[PDB]
Image 1 (cartoon, rainbow, N blue to C red):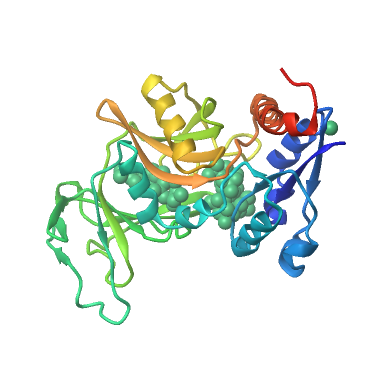
Image 2 (cartoon, helix red, strand yellow):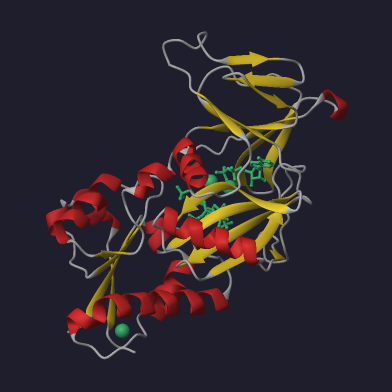
Length: 318
Ligand SMILES: O=P(O)(O)CP(=O)(O)O[C@@H]1[C@@H](OP(=O)(O)O)[C@H](OP(=O)(O)CP(=O)(O)O)[C@@H](OP(=O)(O)O)[C@H](OP(=O)(O)O)[C@@H]1OP(=O)(O)O
Ligand SMILES: Nc1ncnc2c1ncn2[C@@H]1O[C@H](COP(=O)(O)OP(=O)(O)O)[C@@H](O)[C@H]1O
Ligand SMILES: [Mg+2]
Ligand SMILES: [Mg+2]
Ligand SMILES: [Mg+2]
């Protein structure tokens, strides 16, 4: 009898090129059958009617009913590749940062500004023309201001007077742009934010993609904060630069993968001041447009499934 690997995510993710490429390769495993849960079923059917699986690959994106996935996993008790309860915490930057700190992972110095919706005026924020003070902690410009919702990508950077003042407003990339300059020098006055020190990079972000704690692919892309113009190649794909992680960074990836219990996990590294700082943990994410990654990821996931489940299925596996 076959080991069933169930894929439970929104259709946009389940039918994505990287997903289809990887699932095709996982299916090549002799004792593995892949079942992709239909979006209509995920959204409209009670969990009791969802397909059975022995191993569940499931992850949140916009519109995904995480409560249902959690309930399904509790009902069927499959082997879970990416822990579902942790995906609530991944949606909250405050929770992400707390986990990183607890794990001895270097991250930007930061402070949380929580605003009670009823009292916007009763906050712990003092603003100077070249700095902010949050719960008593001072951040000189440049500093970064992030919505506490990790799903909210309206991240702002504030320039010091010596650099011309104003701000850089980042957003989910659309077409040719990932950010825009604003003459606004004052911080946002409604909502809750994390304020953090600006880490000076060479102008790129390092994007890391784990497949288990012992495998991580990295690449670099232009930081959206630079000027906001997206670099695209002859085919319309965003330009990426080769990266090889050093020993320290390979350990960071190991830590992030295990700490968040996300076998497949994307996160960002800022290479600054001779160190590497995690600034964002995104959970489930595949590398795009790398055939070798497709090969590696499918092989590792298949091996994880076989290692974990082959004994109870009485299947030979060395
Ligand atoms: O796919 P589209 O519609 O053309 C927009 P895009 O090309 O910017 O795709 C990005 C995707 O956005 P949506 O799926 O929400 O549209 C992100 O989605 P999200 O996680 O920021 C928001 P969602 O999960 O709610 O969709 C994330 O995709 P993924 O990480 O979910 O695979 C990201 O991936 P990276 O961060 O760059 O690795 C993708 O960027 P790219 O494909 O250029 O790499
Ligand atoms: N502390 C920081 N110092 C310098 N740049 C930062 C810092 N935090 C974020 N950035 C820049 O802003 C971008 C978006 O921030 P990030 O925390 O990755 O949010 P998102 O969840 O929207 O991707 C990063 O890729 C990086 O270029
Ligand atoms: Mg097969
Ligand atoms: Mg990021
Ligand atoms: Mg993020």
